[PDB]
Amino acid sequence: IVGGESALPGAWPWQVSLHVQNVHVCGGSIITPEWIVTAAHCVEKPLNNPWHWTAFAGILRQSFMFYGAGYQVEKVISHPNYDSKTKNNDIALMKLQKPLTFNDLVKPVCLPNPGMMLQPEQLCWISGWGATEEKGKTSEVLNAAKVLLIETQRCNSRYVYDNLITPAMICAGFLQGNVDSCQGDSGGPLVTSKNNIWWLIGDTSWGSGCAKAYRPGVYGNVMVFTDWIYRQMRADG
Amino acid sequence: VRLYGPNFILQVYSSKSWHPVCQDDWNENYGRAACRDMGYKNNFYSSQGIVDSTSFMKLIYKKLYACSSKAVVSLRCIACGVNLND
Ligand SMILES: *C(=O)c1ccc(CCN)cc1
Image (cartoon, rainbow over all chains, first blue to last red):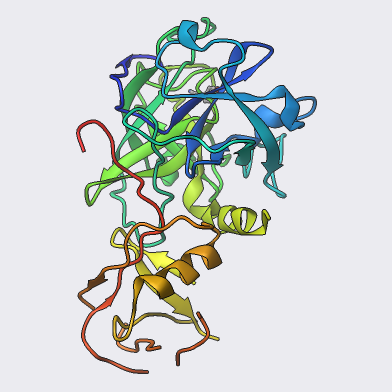
C-alpha cells in the first residue's frame, strides 16, 4: 500500500498474510472459517502445492507472526481460465486444514451478490503488507488506503491500460497516482461498504509499477467469479 | 439459486428470468438447505423476510413453481461484512 496508513486492530479482520518459507508473499481474504480468496498468480508453479503455504489472520505486524503459529493450507484451487500471460481470471482459493476461530480481530468479508449497483467511482478500501514505495520491501505493519473505482472505459484508454482490461478485471486508484497497491499486496482485498456491509469487490492482481500517474491497480472482479467460488466450496467434501 | 443485491434476496432461475421466493411458509430449516446448496456447509446466519419482478416462487429447492402472499426471503448464510466501526 503506497500512500495509506497503518490499519487499526480489527478494521480489516478478513485480511490474512500468506507465507512461504517463513515470509509474507501474498495477501488473501477470509470468506469462511476454512476458505480464503487470493490471486492465481501467487500460486503458480512452483507454489501450486498447498504444503508451502501458511496463513496468519488477526495479526497486524509481521514480527508477531511466529513460525509454527500459522494455519497450514490444505488445498489450492486456481481458476480454470486463469491466463498468466494477460493475468485474466486471476483468482484462486485456499482451504485451511483447520477452521479459523472468528472473534473481533478475525472475521469474514461478504462475497458480492449480483445487483450490487456500485457507483461508477465507488469508494473502496485496499489493505495489505506490500511495499510502501515502488521496489520497496514488505511492510512490517498492515496498511490500508481509500481508493475509487476507475471506470473501465477510462482504464482501457490509450493513455492507461489500452484494451488490457477485460470484464473479469476492475481498476481502482487515482490517475494522478500517489495512492495504490504494490507488490506484496497481491491476492489481497479490495472492499466497499454498502447497506452497512463490507463486500469483497476485487482481489489485488496487477498493473505497472506502484503509485505512478496513469498506472492504477487492476483487481480481479470477484463478482464475475462468485459462482465458480460457490461451486468450489460445494464440491469440497 | 442465488442471493440478489445488498439485501440478500433469494432468487431462482427459469427451470431468461430470475424470480424471488415468497416468505409464505419459510423457516430457518428451509434456510439451511439453500445455504448448503450454495456451498456454505453448516454455516447459517439469518433468514428473515423482507418487502417484495412480479412473478414470485412459493413453496428443498425444487418444491416451488407464479404466486403472491406478501414479503420475500432474505437469506444470509454467514455473519460477514462487519468490522471495528461496524
Ligand atoms: C501485486 O502485488 C500487485 C498488484 C498490483 C500492482 C499495481 C499497482 N499499480 C502491483 C503489484
